[PDB]
Length: 109
Image (tube, rainbow, N blue to C red; front, side, top):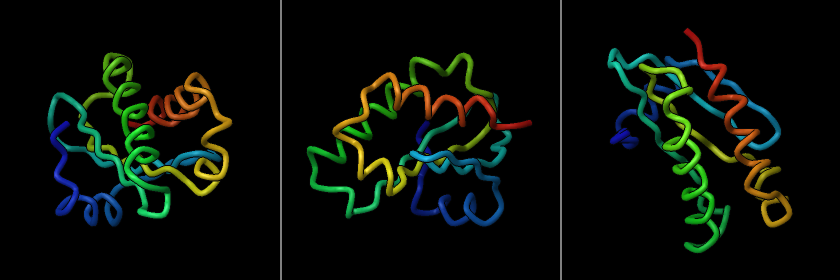
């Protein structure tokens, strides 16, 4: 998952596909590899280091533990949505996991 966002975010956004739910947008494109790579784009307005780092930790953990079931061969960008910033402190880890995994497991084909 060393996805280098500064170069590849534009390309994924323009050429990839997207899925979303109330908490996340996930953008994805085929990478031509036998593994997927993750990047996380957290808007500055989501908060200071503690808050943004908490979200990024959760996201990294969910991807790492679930790599074996997430489809292979995609570059994936996870973007938290306004509603997740609104609600963060009231959403527990298992809900974040559920909501993220439902999009990740639908990346096709």
